[PDB]
Figure 1: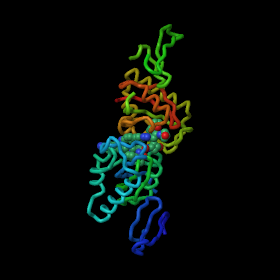
Figure 2 (figure 1 turned 45 degrees about the vertical axis):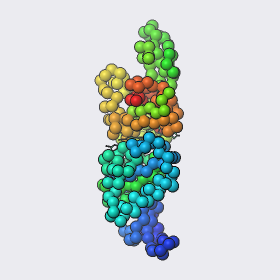
Figure 3 (figure 1 turned 180 degrees about the vertical axis):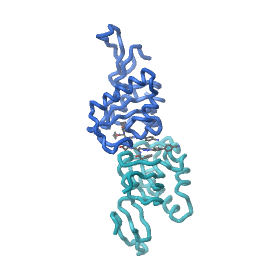
Figure 4 (figure 1 turned 30 degrees about the vertical axis):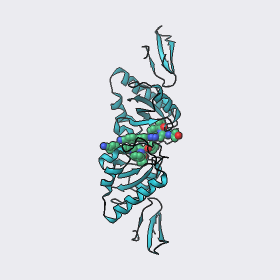
Length: 145
Length: 145
Ligand SMILES: N#Cc1ccc(-c2ccc(-n3cc(C[C@H](NC(=O)C4(c5ccccc5)CC4)C(=O)N[C@H]4C[C@@H](O)C4)nn3)cc2)cc1
Ligand SMILES: N#Cc1ccc(-c2ccc(-n3cc(C[C@H](NC(=O)C4(c5ccccc5)CC4)C(=O)N[C@H]4C[C@@H](O)C4)nn3)cc2)cc1
């Protein structure tokens, strides 16, 4: 019902779930803007990233589809409680923020690349995005404030 | 005569000076390609910028002429030693690289807009640009590596 949400059916299980077309998040439960938000992220870069390099690898060669598989694995592990978002960011994020558990600090509109901004402002506090595609790569976003 | 450097005559002084038509650097003293360079910048946006918005201001309304006056003013404070480049970038850059004292990190050709890229690769390590004009606004570039 709320802006951007779709009620859908898994094509494998028939299970009802909810998908947000601004954050790309999905959740089983039916769902129910701030001047500034604070977000942490986990970035997985790919060969078409604007800067296909990070602390992890001088030259990033994984495809966009490989980056998306990695992101989807992190999301599964976070949603299941098997892993912490911020600990996965610290270990695997292709970002200089990985060291700060993926914290990018507070921002208003006008600072972040538009897809990351749109997802960040549409999250609830404590909520995680789905895969968010930017010029930089693929992100998961955790709104912290 | 390193790349883009040329000799000129000061009308008012009578003395030879040096100007770089790629970096817009100018200096009395005679001066003197890697895969990657590391540069810091100070960006001043204007109402005609590709994205008239930054972490400093939702709506950037200053004119291109006013943006250039601010840039010339900052270059003056830097060269006089009244302000470090880092202190002015931290306070007044319209790029959120202000958080990292203007540091954009290491990049290769292909990532940055051509006038910024060309200036960045034409600077030697430690050197600073004059006003560099992009679609994003007006930059002072400092090559750090
Ligand atoms: N220790 C430590 C430490 C070190 C570094 C950080 C860190 C903190 C903040 C950032 N960051 C980067 C950005 C800007 C940005 N970038 C982005 O818009 C996005 C992004 C892409 C890639 C990496 C990080 C952010 C969101 C999409 C970017 O590409 N912006 C463009 C200019 C145009 O108008 C959109 N803002 N903040 C980057 C790094 C934090 C902690
Ligand atoms: N803490 C922290 C922190 C916060 C932010 C950053 C930060 C890091 C990197 C960037 N950045 C922006 C860009 C895009 C680039 N952009 C550009 O080419 C230019 C640019 C404009 C505006 C801002 C920054 C760069 C040089 C002209 C651009 O516009 N490129 C175009 C695509 C076409 O092929 C040329 N790449 N990296 C922006 C911000 C780093 C650290």
